[PDB]
Length: 163
View 1 (tube, rainbow, N blue to C red):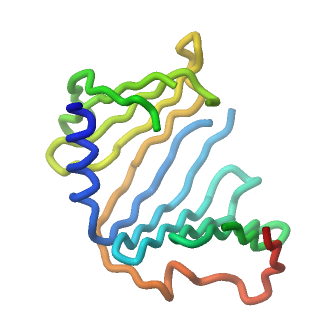
View 2 (tube, one colour):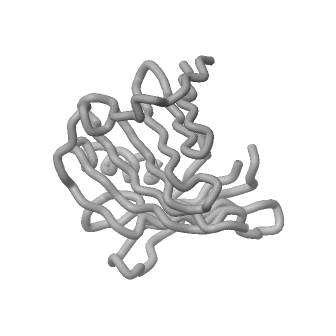
């Protein structure tokens, strides 16, 4: 239940607008910028790496999800883990809580949460043998101000694929 308390602290601590840089491996390198405007229930992810995703972006709202595919100029419009607190570990950003949980494309995961300023720092997904399937780190983070005009922007010439 301690994990739930931590997650609750994170949710409350990130109730204002923020942005971050996510980098890791999934083998290929994944790099993206993330934007959140909680009060408007808006989220945007912009991809930088790998080459197949470079330029793509995803916009999430309470109602629908937009997935822009840069190379094909298509805008696709479409309508859990039992985490437990294992303990703490010192990370570059400082002391963090290490949450662990079992269980559909992975066997278990590790979620690292910064203690001083409750927010995610790293997500690690493991298979049955403990092999890393994905290791994504939040390498940059900043609280800021964002607007719907910014997060809902899209290429005017995008071709719509409506699900």
